[PDB]
Amino acid sequence: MQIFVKTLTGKTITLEVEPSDTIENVKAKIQDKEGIPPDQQRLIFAGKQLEDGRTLSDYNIQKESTLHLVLRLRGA
Amino acid sequence: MQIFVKTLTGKTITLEVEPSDTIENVKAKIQDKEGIPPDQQRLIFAGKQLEDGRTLSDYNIQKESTLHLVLRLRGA
Amino acid sequence: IDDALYSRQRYVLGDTAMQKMAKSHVFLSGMGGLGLEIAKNLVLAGIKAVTIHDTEKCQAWDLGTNFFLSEDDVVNKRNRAEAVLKHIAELNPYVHVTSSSVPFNETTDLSFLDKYQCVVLTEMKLPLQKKINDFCRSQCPPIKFISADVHGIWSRLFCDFGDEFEVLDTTGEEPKEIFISNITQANPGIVTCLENHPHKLETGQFLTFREINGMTGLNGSIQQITVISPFSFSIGDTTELEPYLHGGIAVQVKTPKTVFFESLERQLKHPKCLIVDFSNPEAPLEIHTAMLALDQFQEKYSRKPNVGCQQDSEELLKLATSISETLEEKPDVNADIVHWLSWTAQGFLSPLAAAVGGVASQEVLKAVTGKFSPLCQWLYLEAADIVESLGKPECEEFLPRGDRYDALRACIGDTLCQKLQNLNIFLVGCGAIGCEMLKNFALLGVGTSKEKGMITVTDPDLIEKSNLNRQFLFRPHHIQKPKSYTAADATLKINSQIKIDAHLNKVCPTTETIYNDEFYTKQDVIITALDNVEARRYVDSRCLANLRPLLDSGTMGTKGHTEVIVPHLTESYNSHRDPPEEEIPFSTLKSFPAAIEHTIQWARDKFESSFSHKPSLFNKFWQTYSSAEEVLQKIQSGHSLEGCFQVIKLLSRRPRNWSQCVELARLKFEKYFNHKALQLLHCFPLDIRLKDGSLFWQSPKRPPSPIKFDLNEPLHLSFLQNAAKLYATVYCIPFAEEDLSADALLNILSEVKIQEFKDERNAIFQLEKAILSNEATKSDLQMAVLSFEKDDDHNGHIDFITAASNLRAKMYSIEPADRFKTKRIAGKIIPAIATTTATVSGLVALEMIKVTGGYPFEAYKNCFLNLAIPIVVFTETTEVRKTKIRNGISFTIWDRWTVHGKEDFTLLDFINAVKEKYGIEPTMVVQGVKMLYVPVMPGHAKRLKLTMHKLVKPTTEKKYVDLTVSFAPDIDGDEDLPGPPVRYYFSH
Amino acid sequence: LEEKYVAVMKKLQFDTFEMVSEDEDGKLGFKVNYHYMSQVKNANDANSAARARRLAQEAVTLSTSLPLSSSSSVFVRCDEERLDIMKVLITGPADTPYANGCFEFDVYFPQDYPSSPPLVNLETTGGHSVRFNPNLYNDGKVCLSILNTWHGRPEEKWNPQTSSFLQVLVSVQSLILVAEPYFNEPGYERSRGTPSGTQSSREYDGNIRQATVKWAMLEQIRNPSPCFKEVIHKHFYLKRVEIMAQCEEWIADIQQYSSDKRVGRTMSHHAAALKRHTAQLREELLKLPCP
Ligand SMILES: O=P(O)(O)O[C@H]1[C@H](OP(=O)(O)O)[C@@H](OP(=O)(O)O)[C@H](OP(=O)(O)O)[C@@H](OP(=O)(O)O)[C@H]1OP(=O)(O)O
Ligand SMILES: *P(=O)(O)OC[C@H]1O[C@@H](n2cnc3c(N)ncnc32)[C@H](O)[C@@H]1O
């Protein structure tokens, strides 16, 4: 199933994944599609900073909600 | 094709370009080695200032050609 | 070294340069314009001993070439060397100057010349010059040989430093510092630079290394490098060393360079020239051939060619043809060069002389110090473009008329001089550039026509001790006087016909009222001497509003640039961007310094906040509220007050005497230099690690360290004295200088304890305590508000700032800085030298002639220079750019649309008029920074039915205003198309 | 309930207010406290024109794109004659230590805009007495990568063509306000889940909670700013009961760690401060009239 996710440039990514997509598999897939390292990929949604191990359905929320990201916090 | 960019203060920069490249891409290549933004740099060849939107073939730039990088000063 | 007169020079050169140029002897021959200007330049440099020489006498023709001669000198027929020795002696008391008139010929003994170390020759016959070069070069050590000559619009320059010359610094650019990320124990070793920050280096350069973990053997060693990638390179074998752990700093190491020269005679057969215009690289060889042919003709006929004498022209052409084949390269012959040289062989041109003199003085500096790379080995400057646009002028216009301007008429003719005498030029700024501006203009006799021709200068600045180093127009008895008035008084001596207006105004939008557009249109050309880009942009926008020619230049140190703008031909000054100083996050500045400049900036900001912001806030607070009991009641009633906590804390901590201020300084030192490190280490232990396990306190961060106080440390005592005196000055507490003695301060601190390291009610309690102590008097709510002064030696600003910066470096294990560098960085002082400014002044004065000529777009040039190489370039200026919008409508930067309206004229009327006249509807209207109609913001829709006189609220003195308009993009969601400037008149 | 909250307040997201009055001499008379006196008064160059077009385009987006929700909402006021004088207030996100807060900012547009990122500062600093978030300096300094420029990483910095004001608003409202700002400091996320890190997080969160209870509500209501006055009166009026409920939950949670010894005394001090704040806060809410 596909998804909506937006970024700094606002790309609303829409790509098919699995219902048990573990967030480490999500990091792998993100580095497949873009090659960006998972260390910058601190995915956040529904008030939860995503931890790798559990699957997509392990959180009980499902697809199509526009998700977004936070960087590793660099200081001012 | 090989070209040289000699800035004032004697620093020499080596560049790889091909005819048909656009002046703006040629100057953006400078940033990868110097950090100077494209909008901040003026480059001169054969007594003419290279205008944006043109290509190297228009100015007849060939192998081992030399381009100068110049800046304005503030003191007085 | 008296810093008050050589502060800029020290930063330009360095102490070794001043030490070497001391105890130096230079011989110069020929009291022409070139000799005079080189002499003034070197005296401004400040050589201990210089000897001049000349055997000729004053002439009426010498008036147009010498700016220190007088009509009395010509009347008395004095030797040219004697009549100027006094004036040049006035420049520097520390410079000893000697004059000589010993006859020189083939039989003259040259053994006496060994006393000097360098020789400068001008207006000398060629074979004698060759003989002198041979004698000088045969010496052990050889004496530097320098020669230059000028004929009309032609200049020749040659240099010879012997078989081998040594350079102690090729470029003069400070080496950079990097951070080591990874190193491989490989043969050859591979070094990985930190993330980003490409090294920008080159293969073969040497770097020294330090604080490398694992390979302690690589610390203190110098390795020649081999660039591999933008962020990596190669070093020697490292397999025999320990594994790399972390850290490492590499800095480039400069290397002395040896160069070589040749004899004059050998170089004549194949000169090693330097190219300044890549458009015609073949020109210098032809010019050298023409100069050699001219020398041959002059030797043969003992005379210069006559203007209009075609036989002289063909004879010179035949001589050049004979010479050209003889050359090693065997070049061709440029007939027009020969014709023009023969036509104007007897003229003299001032700005070319000035530029040649500046570059020659710089090369003499290179010879005496070896601090820069010398020029090798030839130079030829020329300004033929001015005479190229003349078509075919007659020789009669060049004929002399028996005046001081005979040479200039022989150069360009009488007509251009007549056009020159009628120019109304405006000058802004009166720095070092403005003085030589005025000197050159006096030499040109600009504006001397009674009916027309005017010069205006405005500068609010006064005369300062350091200004005399660069500004020769001013004397030590002129200190604290308007620059404009003193400069005008100095310049009017040379020529009585000068019509000059001098003002103390600073150009700015507020003063624009005196500078109305009628005044601008009255002027014909404007020259800039500004030091800041904001005023430059403002002046650009002013001149563009009048379509007026403008000239701009700028110099730092050994670099300089010149720019020319012409109405309807080129782009604006604002058409290009300038790189501002980069920003530093406090994440660095406040907490994680990595360089001495960071500590300098932090100390400067702390000083500013403490001694400027805080007293002003306190006084504003206590002038807003008259009574302190009133404030106490308002606090007790729960009312909020702005900045109340800070002011009450300051007042409760108000010292009353000298000892209290001393204790305050001591505790401030304790807090600043001891407790901060403790708190930072408490929040972050030295062993704290990151997610990867890498140390948080890794590069570029440096761990701090608390410092224990010691009065016996001179730095600590100096900083304490600075802090105490600043506190006493701020709090209006008088004191005696004997209190600053170390013994008295020790007596004060011998009973001083220090607290160890670890709201509204307390503030109210302190306020009540102050009230019951009668500490709320009107005098108590006051302290002096201070301003930074880097030019005062006793105020202690620099002393305190340097001490604080050194300490802040110290606890972070950073190398401190001396007083001079700290002062230069804090004041952001711009180094400069007389040679560069003189050369750029000559260049801009020369280009002014082309500006006057009304020549086509191809005649003008812009030049950028860096004599440290040395390097000079001449390029054609940017052409004007076209901007189309829609429906085939296009415009330029010079185009301006105009619409006349009425008193009942409305916004819909304006839209209808503009759309009718130009076919496009203005989608928005804004007057400068205040909007007039934006449909997005609610309520601007009702603005369409308003009187435009009402909506604008203009000033009566102006009958028109200029507004900004835009137009809807063809595709919605895109940025609106910008509109050309529109000038609206309130009435016809 | 939340439907009514969003419905009523949608008309007040974007609006305008008059702050500067110019006399006959051109002097700038500011009617309210603004952090940028000197910059506005001194920088009088009108050479910039592209900034006007850029802000005209921005006004279209910012008039409709303002986030508005029960958790957090955006409301902005700007000068009715100038363009570089900004003011904005945000409502604290639900369940955060800054829950249902109200904080003000002052934003100045430089002349060289959009070639440079604008300026911004806090306004509810408590007289600079409170440092709220690692990314929030107590004096009021605001630091954002999209609002600054250095060597660093190219895409993150201020991009004149792509970086937008609304993006800055979103970055602030989202990244600055998080559930656990204690681990915002890099190097502390190494100790996530550890009992010591958890205890330190609890203590820091209690500190933040008591500080925001003191300043973000009581001080705001007692001496409101003229600009966002009616807006805050309406917003705080509706959320009184939930504010009381979360205050009681916080106080009950604060009481749980008073038995500790490592953090017990400071924890109880935070409890006492919170109770003292709530004592007057309840009275103030009971005195609040219906808008
Ligand atoms: O007002 P500033 O010039 O910005 O300096 C202040 C000031 O220090 P000084 O009085 O020594 O100049 C604060 O002290 P108070 O007068 O407010 O008590 C101090 O706060 P602390 O005493 O609580 O340490 C603060 O430091 P910080 O912001 O780290 O708390 C420090 O700021 P700077 O030293 O960075 O200017
Ligand atoms: P350099 O710094 O040697 O000399 C510059 C001089 O120009 C004057 N100046 C600076 N800025 C202005 C403006 N805006 N208007 C008029 N004059 C200006 C400085 O005072 C120096 O004298």
Image: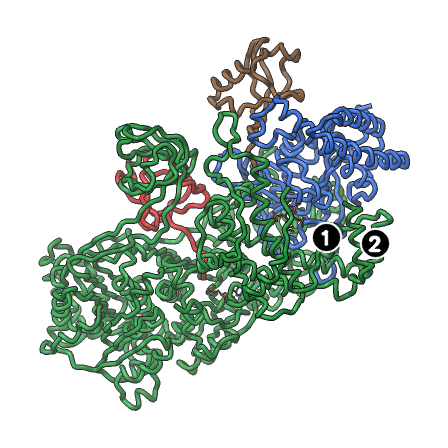
Chain colours: A brown, B red, C green, D blue
Bin the neighbour count of mark 1 within 10 Å (Cα to Cα): few under 14, some 14-19, many 20 and up. some
The amino acid pointed to by label 1 is Lys
Compared across the picture, whether D177 is left or right of C8 comes to: right
- Give the percent coordinates (x, y) of residue C273: 21, 56
Residue C35 seen in the current view: yes
Q: Residue at x 58, y 29 (%)?
A: D188
- Which residue occupies the extreme bottom position in the image? C76
Which residue lies at the image location 29% right of the left edge and 76% below the top edge?
A: C407
Q: Quadrant of residue B30?
A: top left
In this rendered view, identify the residue nearer to me: B56 or C55.
Answer: C55
Seen from the viewer's position, the closer of residues C612 and C309 is C612
Residue A11 marker: none
Q: How many marks?
A: 2
Q: Chain of mark 2?
A: C
Residue C949 visible in rendering: no
Q: Measuring 67% from the left and 66% from the top, which residue is drawn there?
A: C732
Q: Residues within 10 Å of mark 2 (few under 14, many from 20)?
A: some
Which element type, helix, strand or loop, lies under badge 1? helix
Q: Check the picture and name the quadrant holding the C terminus of chain C.
A: bottom right
* Mark 2 lies on residue: C632
Is the C-beta of the residue carrying label 1 under 8 Å from the nearest atom of ligand 1?
yes
